[PDB]
Length: 82
Length: 64
Image (cartoon, rainbow over all chains, first blue to last red; front, side, top):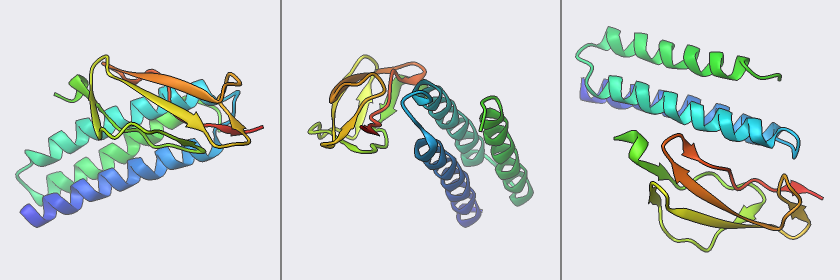
């Protein structure tokens, strides 16, 4: 369970880092305030799901949480134009 | 709790001389753009503030 928790934490962190990186890459002077709001929100989602993961008691729950974190990240991105 | 501090942010086309790795609420961080780059408002420098939400602004500069 410790190893699985570590893997789940890494997956959640890496996905958020990926999407934050994509948000930075596409940023422009005009889009900059979107980038700030979105990145703060993505890091907030990250913290929520890492906290759920650390206290999780089963492997299946970890898989559900990884999936839910990804969906919440993608939903946040969807609130702004591409 | 997670709303009581901010991690050093990712920088893009900018530097900081600040050597802290995490910040308390109301702590600040100064950045400077790489030569040839500017902030979203046209400055070569900025100062950002750690808040409940995260950072007030991010150290991203843009090619002039």
